Length: 191
Image 1 (cartoon, one colour):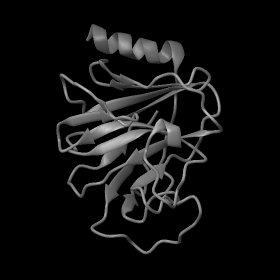
Image 2 (image 1 turned 120 degrees about the vertical axis):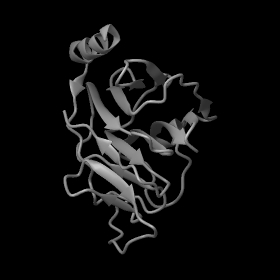
Image 3 (image 1 turned 30 degrees about the horizontal axis):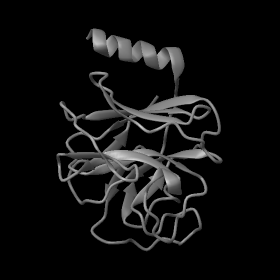
Image 4 (image 1 turned 135 degrees about the vertical axis):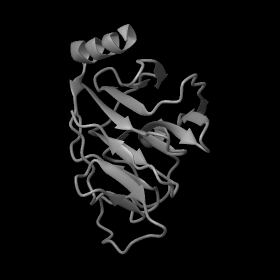
């Protein structure tokens, strides 16, 4: 109510609303990107896709269609009652083919959920989160210049996690990851 209103006014004071669509050319071959490019599901097995260089071959990742090299940006993601997901940003230069650990040291800033109830930030070591109200909708907030990546419950304005301030190298991309085969898709909220 007031908390929702303050969350809305804070987004306006500081952050540009990003209109994020998923790039199917980046998506791991086990992922399905929806025809409107807002939603993500998983297949029972890898589909036959070209191994173009941008595609994540190991990690069940997909990128947005536009990168950020500067400024303050947010987008919101409907996670709904998914039991598993991770979202955030990654550098353009992340490893796409070989496994790397999804950590800030390797150019990934993500948080998410496993097994329905285990909220974690994928810092190294991983940060155990304690979340009083499981979010249905998550806001991702980027400040490129100050090296800030933070996450909020978009419905009640409660804070979830802020990574330590860092120094980004090169463009950042929105990144999305799902490991499970379950009924609820991951869906980006349009700007």
